[PDB]
Amino acid sequence: AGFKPAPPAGQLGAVIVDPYGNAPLTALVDLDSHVISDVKVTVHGKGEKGVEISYPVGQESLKTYDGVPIFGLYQKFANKVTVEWKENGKVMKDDYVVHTSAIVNNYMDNRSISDLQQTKVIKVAPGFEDRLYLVNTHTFTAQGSDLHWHGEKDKNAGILDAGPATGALPFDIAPFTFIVDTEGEYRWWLDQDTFYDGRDRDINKRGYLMGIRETPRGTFTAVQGQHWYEFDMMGQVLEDHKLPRGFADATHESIETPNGTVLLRVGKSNYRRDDGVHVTTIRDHILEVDKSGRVVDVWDLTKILDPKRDALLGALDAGAVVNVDLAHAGQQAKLEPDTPFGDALGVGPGRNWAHVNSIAYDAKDDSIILSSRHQGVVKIGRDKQVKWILAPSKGWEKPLASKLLKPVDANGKPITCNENGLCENSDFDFTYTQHTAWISSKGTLTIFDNGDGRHLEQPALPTMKYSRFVEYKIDEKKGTVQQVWEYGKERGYDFYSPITSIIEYQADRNTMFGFGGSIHLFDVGQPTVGKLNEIDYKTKEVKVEIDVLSDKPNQTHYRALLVRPQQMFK
Amino acid sequence: AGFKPAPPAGQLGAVIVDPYGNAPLTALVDLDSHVISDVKVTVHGKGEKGVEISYPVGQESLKTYDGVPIFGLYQKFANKVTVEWKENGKVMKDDYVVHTSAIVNNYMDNRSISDLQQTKVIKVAPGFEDRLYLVNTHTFTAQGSDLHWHGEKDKNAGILDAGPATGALPFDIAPFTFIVDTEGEYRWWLDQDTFYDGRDRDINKRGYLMGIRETPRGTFTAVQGQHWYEFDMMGQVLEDHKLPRGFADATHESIETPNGTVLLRVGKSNYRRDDGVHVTTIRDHILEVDKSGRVVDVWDLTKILDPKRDALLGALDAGAVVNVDLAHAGQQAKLEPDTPFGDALGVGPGRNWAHVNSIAYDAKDDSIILSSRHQGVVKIGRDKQVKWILAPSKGWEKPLASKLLKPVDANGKPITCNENGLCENSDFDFTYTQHTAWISSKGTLTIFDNGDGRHLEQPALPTMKYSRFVEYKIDEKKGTVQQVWEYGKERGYDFYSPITSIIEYQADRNTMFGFGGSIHLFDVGQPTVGKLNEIDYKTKEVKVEIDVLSDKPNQTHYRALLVRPQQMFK
């Protein structure tokens, strides 16, 4: 006679590159029936300033992989890797040379600047050299959007006409998923064919790979089209679920709860409107599902919030929304009453009236906090009741108006803001077209305030626009909110992300982690900038600033995560 | 233009037959955006003595399916179905006529008696008319076993020779999976293509569909080849996991624990023997895995029990082992020291020394109880230590001998049994080549004692063989075992199942449920009998006896389950 397996490389088994076939900068040391413990892996830096990557490896992982996972390799390089373990109460060590192959971008055309996205390291403080960031970005396919859901023909349409579309099937794009270190080197890559195939027409492998979040096991969830997933840093796909049959179009977020369920943002297909027309709703439903794919609960936001409120909808940059473009960049969006159902700015179920793009679970009262790009930030209870809302007061009717939070200063004294969220004699401002409204380890609400439609108008000039990191403290009993921190207001257009983006508070080194996904988006002909940032919470000093430039002009990035090797292999 | 969806049948949505495409005797009432509760489904009996099936439907199910599930249809029939619910505090009712298509057996050849397995109702006591049994049986493919794992060439083999086989890849057969009512009618069918494709050579869809067990959600797990699954009675495949890479050949059992894990019975691939030869082990490892497919724990039985112990191995009918001779039927198995590694009777890792075929989790001390066909019944701890053994004393060395349970009568007085398990002046006997060693709702240990190799010999004539249901009571602290119940001893060869089979205690009606999967297996040219039974625990009266006859001669059944519609749709 046959062909023998790879023989052993040292004192354990063979060292296999990319055992699952989805993560070419990983490897695996076959255990070959050895019984070991106390395992530590080190991957050595490339050259003089190269970052070394180091992590322990738990028993579950050794058993799961039947070997020792090797994460952190450089591409096309003779990686030097050390593995240490205990075996029969004796200390053991092996040094391996692990050659790798290349990273491939399978989606290139005349818009391509080059195959990979470029990195520019701007600033790395001391004691931050070891940081790693997983960048969740994407790259245009040659074809663009080729598929639509079919809907119901509306009453007042041509006798002869073909059926309309519905939903958001065209929200579809090739992934570009990697990890970057502080020398700007790629240290991990998730093969684009792991989940996506843009040449075939198998909707099972289509969509927009989004909402990558860690789990209590140090693995990650994600969504893409009409499926959701779980995977690990060796590239093993651990779960793959079709959405339940009533739902479609999962985007933006996926988060595991502590109860072993997962929260997803979807649309409802075959939603019967009060006028009896069926549509696939846009980005306005939430699912709690178990690890079986079954639905544990569903929040239908069309009956909980207000699909008629156009206060923020009418104030937006038509050029944005990810989507994008562009002849109409800068221009304020003029709503129309005859806007056909679809992924379009508008009111009512079957249009993009809410565009919820983040989810967080509050364990303390079994509730969920949501970021609605076009309405504000809300908490809704298990009981399907609104608990509070963080938004400008304009447009809200009762009973919902009554749940708006009242702003207050450090001593708890009301702050005067008009119905557009413009406050006087304060740093306090609300969020507009925001993202990632999550719960910090401190118990506060952190948000990335993108800043389109700030104060419910377009400004006089496009460049008078800014984005903020911002943190709030909320008293639920009293119904008040206090801005306790902010950043970015002063950096102007060069730090403005009209779309996407994220922040998350890091307690380990007291920093605020940021990723601005859409900087310079509207600079026609230029790469879009994804700017990784760690800001000192105390001093506001920049500790890390790294820029990722898109491989094609005018191509937004979605999010990034700060990942930690220590937690990857439990 | 287009084609419209099926219109509404009555007051909800359309009634879709086989929505998921794997269970043709099911249907679904689309919810069409209606908000309902208190759902109850009734499927009417066919004709005069036809059994009616009725169940409630919980909210999770309505949301999961976006509709009301309909279970219990007859094939090729105008099924009459009633659905009742509450909507806007009003009571509601719809009567539907649901036409079905046929059941198909896709695996037929000259051996075939007819396409379906025949049922013969023998006895149905009053108050047992409503019982349903899920039959886990199988049907031969034209090709038989066509595939082997490749192994390592052993030292003392021909220079020119090809590599050997290893493992148990040939354990491969088409499934045949249905639910039968007490009129002997098929009321549910699982499409054979759900998991199996015996004409293609994709090993992902090969194996022996086994170990079907219910879960806390009213769904079922199962194994087949190199994957494990979860499915529900609407035929939705909820989970599908590849085995972890170190393991192969999952058969016999899959059971969800209360900790959200699942227990599986596998072999280990690339197992390094002490002589340095690599093999795939046979049926001698246990995995706890999570819903992510990851390994939580592993029990390697080659280091826990005694792979050298041939006390029972040498006493077996060569005609059995599932697998089936049958030219050497009746004959005693003569072990050889040069038996090449494989699915073969023999000692040591790489042969079938243990043939473990059932697993149970003891939540009281976080341990597992195992049925080893070829060694006996053992409890092993989380700590990988043997806690006790229920078997004849011959062949066991220390430290294991010391864990053997000592038999006792109702007053706790020792019972005298020789090393072969023959007892004097008692009804007490051990189990031989047994199956399903499970924990009843009473806290006792129930077992199907097939009875091949009884008293560690073949009898003088082949028909001097019998099978028992049997229940034991164990004092772990004292190290003793008491037989407290038995049945079938008196029924002789006609109730003898040399292989497979199952029992389980039903507390709802104080019965012992049983399935004899291999009756008349050795009758050349005759269908094999799978006999479903419910025996009154108190009186020993037969309450249900129903016979399933195989669609080809000499083709064993594996198991059946008593299923309860009340629990299927939580």
Image (tube, coloured by chain):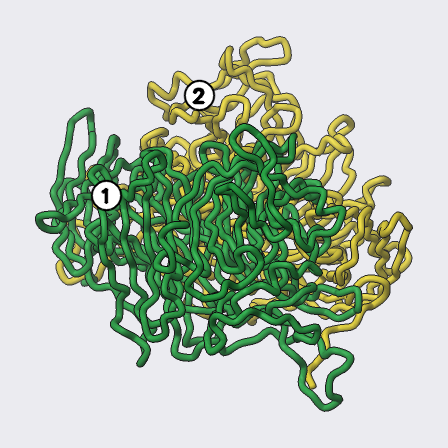
Chain colours: A green, B yellow
Q: Are marks 2 and 1 in contact (CB under 8 Å)?
A: no
Instruction: Give the residue pinned by disc 2.
Output: B387
> From what the image shows, is residue A251 above or below residue B320?
below
Instruction: State the residue in front, B428 or B96.
Output: B96
Q: Amino acid at mark 1?
A: Asp
Residue A564, x across and y down, in percent: 32, 41
Residue B135, x across and y down, in percent: 64, 51
What chain letter is assigned to the residue under label 1?
Answer: A
Residue B262 visible from this viewpoint: no
Q: Is residue B288 left or right of residue B19?
A: left
What chain letter is assigned to the residue under label 2?
Answer: B
Residue pictured at 56% horizontal, 25% vertical: B429
Instruction: Give the residue pinned by disc 1.
Output: A32
| Numbered circles on residues, count | 2
Residue pictured at 36% horizontal, 43% vertical: A64
Residue B1 visible from this viewpoint: yes
Q: Residues within 10 Å of mark 2 (few under 14, many from 20)?
A: many
Secondary structure at numbered mark 2: strand
Instruction: State the residue in front, B211 or A123.
Output: A123
